[PDB]
Structure formats: C-alpha cells, structure tokens
Length: 37
Ligand SMILES: [Cd+2]
Ligand SMILES: [Cd+2]
Ligand SMILES: [Cd+2]
Ligand SMILES: [Cd+2]
Image (tube, rainbow, N blue to C red):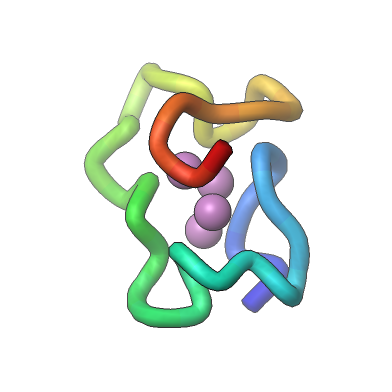
C-alpha cells in the first residue's frame, strides 16, 4: 500500500494492514525494516 519507506505498494506483509505501524521511532522511515524482510 506504499504505506512506508522500508516498503513498497506490493509489500505482502503490509498489504494486510502495515506490520510496521508500531515501529514508531523504529525503521518506518529508514529505507529497510526488520519484519517484512
Ligand atoms: Cd515498512
Ligand atoms: Cd512492509
Ligand atoms: Cd507498511
Ligand atoms: Cd516491516
């Protein structure tokens, strides 16, 4: 859902309901994250 920085519009894990939502000061913005990879 393009919902991120770590993730695109095709991100399976997020396509559900954005895994990273609670990654507040986490990797949300930091180009790459530690759930979806
Ligand atoms: Cd993400
Ligand atoms: Cd994701
Ligand atoms: Cd997301
Ligand atoms: Cd993630």
